[PDB]
Amino acid sequence: SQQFNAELEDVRSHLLAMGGLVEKQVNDAVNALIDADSGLAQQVREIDDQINQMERNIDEECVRILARRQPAASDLRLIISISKSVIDLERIGDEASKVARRAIQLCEEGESPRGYVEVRHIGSQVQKMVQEALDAFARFDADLALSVAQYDKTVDREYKTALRELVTYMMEDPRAISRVLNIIWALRSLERIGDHARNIAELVIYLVRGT
Amino acid sequence: QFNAELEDVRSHLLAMGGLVEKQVNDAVNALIDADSGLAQQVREIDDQINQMERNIDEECVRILARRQPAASDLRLIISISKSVIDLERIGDEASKVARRAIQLCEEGESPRGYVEVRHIGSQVQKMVQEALDAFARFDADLALSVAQYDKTVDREYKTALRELVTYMMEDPRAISRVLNIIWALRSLERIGDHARNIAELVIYLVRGT
């Protein structure tokens, strides 16, 4: 041991580094959509490969660590929280990358007459949820983690009311359907990003509380 | 010991996979046939699926508690735990398809989309069955064929969407019904990505990368 806990901090810090890269993808995707910025949107998709390769590198790392002799219960909880959470980070990065596709599409089609304030609002919240879940993991802080998980309720709630606004608007202005659907798909991806931040928070709870 | 609990966990996985395939089949059929009873069946199983997932995940964690496994054994258990998340996501997307089927029963049938739902639905159903069969037999050839087919589903989804959108502008009164077909199609495409994910676990376990 006891350099087993070095290699353990190394995989913890690799998680954090992945999370940081993914959080920046969320930031850039949202800005891309709002700013009708194709270049920024493409830059986000091109990161998604590095993110997938980070996830693979972390999974193998968890494998090697585990392979060396049985971990104590708390350590096992940590490795398990890491390997499940890189899946969440990967799915966050993939959703970011879908938002960036919507961004490009809206550049081609013209802006939606509705939904930008909602995208920005939900996006900034869900990006916060990601920072907080990572900060919570980084500090074994199951208090913060709990509130993240709880805030997901209000995000899903905001999503359903924005959907209402946007569907009823589509029925009033059918010419805008293609553009409104793009905002709606982007909002659905932002909601999922918040669902995954919540999952990573719940893993931090399990890690800390033991359950 | 490992061999025994591995077969235990593998045995629960295959049962879970079997229900989920039936869920997808029931949910696609519910939509095409306007059959809300069958959609109800999809939603019922979904609770069992989530149970199986939780159980299977606990078993994996206990197995990881126990030994010190060879790397290759760790890979396998970690991949099993991943694959049950995919199976749960598939189950959940099937439930969404069922919900859409119910709404459509209420609204009367959409003027458009059922041909594409049958088409994409049957392909994605096949992808799941093959992904699971490939996993059951560690057949990496089959796995790779599944993963690569996803691109054609995504392509078919994108052309279906374009045509359904333009149709909704030609006929605004169908908006609510057509949106339901679109949401269902979104779930099916998602089911395809999850079958692709399971097939890719097989490729990784067999070929390394």
Image (cartoon, coloured by chain):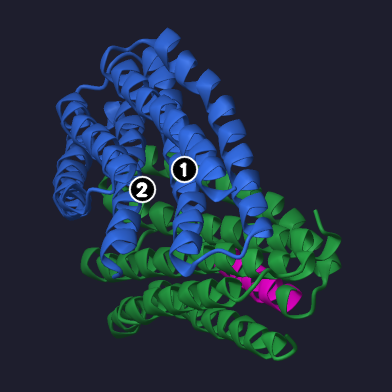
Chain colours: A green, B blue
Alpha-carbon neighbours of circle 1 within 10 Å: few (<14), some, or many (≥20)? some
Residue A138 falls in which quadrant of the image? bottom right
Q: Which residues are magenta?
A: A121-136
* The stretch drawn in magenta includes residue A122: yes
Say which quarter of the image contains residue B38. Answer: top left
- Where A1 sits versus B134, above or below? below
- Judging by the rendered image, the residue that carries numbered circle 2 is B194
Chain letter of mark 1 equals B
Residue shown at 56% from the left, 72% from the top: A67
Disc 2 from disc 1: Cα separation: 7 Å
Is residue A190 or residue B110 the one in the foreground?
A190
Q: Give the x, y percent position of residue B66.
A: 67, 57
Mark positioned earlier in the residue sequence (2 or 1): 1
Q: Which x, y percent locates residue A123?
A: 55, 67
> Which amino acid type is shown beneath numbered disc 2?
His
Residue at the spot 42% in from the left edge and 52% down from the top edge: A184
Please, what is the dominant secondary structure of the magenta stretch? helix
Helix or strand or loop: what does disc 2 sit on? helix
Task: Tell me the number on the disc at residue B89.
Answer: 1
Residue A184 visible? The answer is yes
